[PDB]
Amino acid sequence: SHMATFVELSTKAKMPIVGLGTWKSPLGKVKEAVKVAIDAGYRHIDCAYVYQNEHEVGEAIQEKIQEKAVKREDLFIVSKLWPTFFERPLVRKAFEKTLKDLKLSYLDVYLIHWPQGFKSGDDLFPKDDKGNAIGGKATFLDAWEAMEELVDEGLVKALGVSNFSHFQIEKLLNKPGLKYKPVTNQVECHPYLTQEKLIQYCHSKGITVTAYSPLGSPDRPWAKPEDPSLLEDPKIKEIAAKHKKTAAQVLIRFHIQRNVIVIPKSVTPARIVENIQVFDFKLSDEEMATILSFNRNWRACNVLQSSHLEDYPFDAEY
Ligand SMILES: NC(=O)c1ccc[n+]([C@@H]2O[C@H](COP(=O)([O-])OP(=O)(O)OC[C@H]3O[C@@H](n4cnc5c(N)ncnc54)[C@H](OP(=O)(O)O)[C@@H]3O)[C@@H](O)[C@H]2O)c1
């Protein structure tokens, strides 16, 4: 029986500092992964419309609620709005699909998944004849307006953003008539991409950070063998040995000690349990400084080529 520390959001809601990632968790494996996580004591599950598995997540959650293994109010369910759905009627239709698949009556956090709006229609990844991403009509500020309505209606408890630079968050925080502030910014982060300035900025604004791909996303389709590999880094494994822990557990604990929420994905029952066993050790200040020194400014998750649309987040220094 495990419990992740709570990080307090600006709304006073309590967000578990470790959650289960579900990107690439296949149909036919994700349902069990979520059951196992809930049995182990995970309460935060990270989800998205684009992962196309929310209905199996919804099945797992419903079954554990019926079983009385957990109550809804102790779960913390996060989903995201995909940028082909920024137009107002579409915000509400995409949201309703996620909430239906997940079989819930409310979400704990709903995120803008990426800051650039894309052409609406059937394709999730609309591209021109040359394969460049096609921009849409509505901006992330337009979508945010429609998302605030969901909070007014009691269907989402808090809103947040993902893949935002500080410039894009400034634009949001400065929007005229802003009703709700983002409670987290979910971005890639790990010892090869330490995000020092973006974390400093977010915290200074009362915005949490959620670290995605904290293990280096080894299962990402575009991985190349010469790409840095955190889980095989010998200096990470050495610090791990010193604490009698795995590299993955050190990689998860790194974020916990910076007060950054972290969402490792697994569909392997043993690794699910291993990844939440991270509250029985502490990395020394020396060890934190060493791990922080590994920054390479390297992004594993840098596939959208959309740097020719406005609001490309990764051109900014942070
Ligand atoms: N907002 C965004 O744009 C965005 C982008 C990327 C990710 N995310 C979210 O962040 C979550 C985590 O990132 P990610 O899926 O990219 O990658 P990740 O969590 O860095 O790595 C997942 C990979 O590591 C393996 N793994 C898990 N625990 C392990 C352990 N203890 N030892 C060894 N290997 C282990 C998993 O294998 P098995 O599954 O086979 O065990 C899987 O191949 C995602 O699933 C998603 O929910 C969000």
Image (spheres, rainbow, N blue to C red):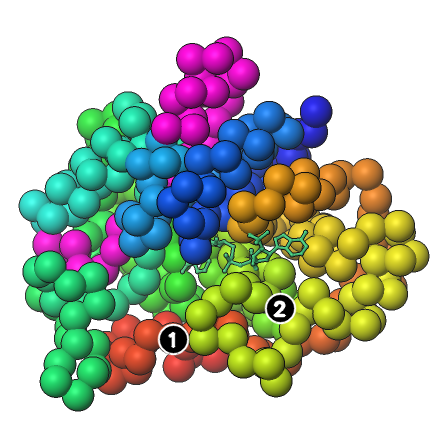
Which of the pair 161/101 is nearer the observer? Answer: 101
Dot 1: element? loop
Number of dots carrying numbers? 2
User: Disc 1 marks which residue?
Assistant: 303
Q: Is residue 210 left or right of residue 150?
A: right
Q: Position of residue 254 (x, y in %)?
A: 71, 56
Whether residue 164 is visible:
yes
Q: Position of residue 57 (x, y in %)?
A: 39, 35
Q: Position of residue 230 (x, y in %)?
A: 68, 69
On screen, 301 above or below 199? below
Name which residue lies at 7% across and 45% down: 89
Dot 2: element? loop
**Classed neighbour count for the residue bearing mark 1: other residues with Cα under 10 Å, few (<14), some (14–19), many (≥20):** few
Q: Is residue 42 left or right of residue 288?
A: left
Q: Quadrant of residue 305?
A: bottom left
CA distance for labels 2 and 1? 19 Å
- Quick check: is 65 in the magenta stretch? yes
- Quick check: is 212 in the magenta stretch? no
Name which residue lies at 69% across and 29% down: 2
Q: Quadrant of the N terminus?
A: top right
Q: Identify which amino acid the numbered label 2 is placed on.
A: Thr
Q: Is residue 95 left or right of residue 60?
A: left
Q: Is residue 276 left or right of residue 37?
A: right
* Tag of residue 194: 2
Q: Identify which amino acid the numbered label 1 is placed on.
A: Val
Name which residue lies at 41% across and 41% down: 28
Which of the pair 22/167 is nearer the observer? Answer: 22
On screen, 22 above or below 239? above
Which residues lie in the magenta part?
59-87
